[PDB]
Structure formats: C-alpha cells, structure tokens
Image: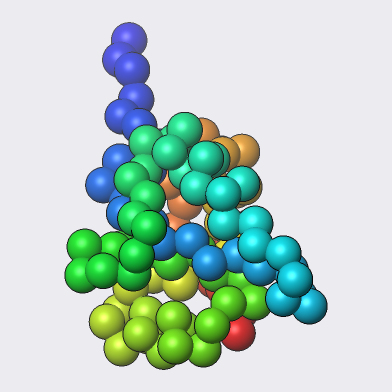
Length: 97
Ligand SMILES: [Cl-]
C-alpha cells in the first residue's frame, strides 16, 4: 500500500525529434508525454539537461550529448517508460545517429 513516484522524476529532457526528411519537428508531441510522466523539459540544451530524446536531429546535439555524458534516448524509450509505468534503463533504447 504505497503510491509510486512520478515515473520520470528528476529527468530534465531536451527534445530534438524530426521527420527523416527534416521537414517536420515533432518535439512538442514528446515534450507533452515527458511532462505527463513528471519530467521537466528544457527549451535549450543547457547544463542542467540529463537526457536528450533524439531522432534525426542535429549532429552538434549528438556530439554535445556524447561529450557531456548526457543520456541519448530514442522516442521508443519514451514509449517503453509509459508502457512499463516505470523509468526504464536508458541503455535499453538508445537513440541512433
Ligand atoms: Cl530497467
């Protein structure tokens, strides 16, 4: 008899999710989902960011995440956290570049 913490408590996410052809930015779709699970979302990739949700984004974002050891996760990671109702290991659903 105890209620769970917000699923993505303490996650501070920057979202860069584009269509493959680069014409459409879907970052708002995923910002909303993250906030509903208790993450904070930053409009900029600043020093407080812990996670970058990345799909077909900018190479500079990829390289900066790698340099800083910020977790680079796919939109599938977001889905799988929602499905599990739990903060799933980021190693399971890495982003691809
Ligand atoms: Cl896990």
